[PDB]
Amino acid sequence: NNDNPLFKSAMVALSLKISIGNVVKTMQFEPSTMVYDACRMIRERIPEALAGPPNDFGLFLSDDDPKKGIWLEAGKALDYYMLRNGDTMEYRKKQRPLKIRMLDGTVKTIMVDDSKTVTDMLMTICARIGITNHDEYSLVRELMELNWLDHGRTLREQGVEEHETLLLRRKFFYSDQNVDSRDPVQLNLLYVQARDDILNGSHPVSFDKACEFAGFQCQIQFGPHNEQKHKAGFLDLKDFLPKEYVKQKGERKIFQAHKNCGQMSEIEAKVRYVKLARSLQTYGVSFFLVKEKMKGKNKLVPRLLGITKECVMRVDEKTKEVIQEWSLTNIKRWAASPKSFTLDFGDYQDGYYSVQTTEGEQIAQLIAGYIDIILKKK
Image (tube, rainbow, N blue to C red; front, side, top):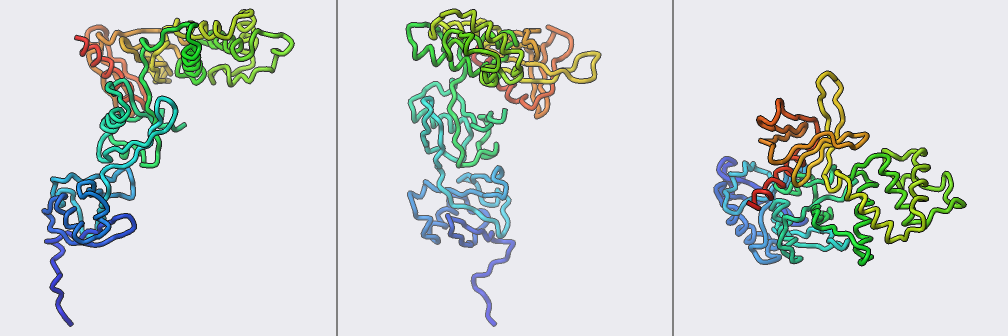
């Protein structure tokens, strides 16, 4: 039957659960307390808060949905964050390991500031491995379209948790690839890259070309065509043709192209493979499958939309013919939403070009990125 000298009204103090690893303690804060001073008071009450230099720790407001967890800023008052009695704050190390697959295919773990955006993290990575031009590179997930990361947002809010390894990826440069039979190791790297892009469909090609490529691929993998062993049914066509072309009728066309190679060496076939790829107007282009509205028709028409350093291009989805091309110079503005992408060509044409796609923000950022480059050369 006593009074409690510790009691303060629920309205004048914030009662928060402070979590450090598996330790939790409830402490009382004046609600205008700055985050950095709250960290001090935490160090005075919880021994596990002393597990490192004091400025290495901060406060993190977790959530049942990990995408909604946020780091608190040191200069903000606690009541800025709309906290209520009983809420939980983690006292957390500000840097955390981020696993990144290097350009040599190995994984390196790099400490990054966990409150920052993907761009900031990329900059920390490039700093650690001696890359000055971080704008030549980006981070992508390794899932599977779903691997794209918006570098102006955080990993956390895009659903990337701390366990996930990301890939460091060099962007495409036409100046990167200059073919020659003198350097077999570099020739093979170029061949593998061009072949993989065709087989996985990121370089879209016609059916006839896909079988031509497969003909060189056969020369490379099997040597000269031998009608005793390279007969109907031999090929696992899924390994030689883009998925949309995996049809038995393609094998006859591949074998024709293979035979046409004669006794051509493995090196010479790799040269021809790479040369044929670079000869196509689709080479090096970043493509997106978008849905177009054609005047007259009610069903939208799937179309390949390609973005390069100097143009936007419409490509037929079945034949891969280049239907139309717009210089980046002749685009007045663009817009993206989660469901569409629209281009305004000012007085170069009547009507906007507006398509359905879930990759509109990706398209918009590519266009903006390539336009900024042209500006900086001016």
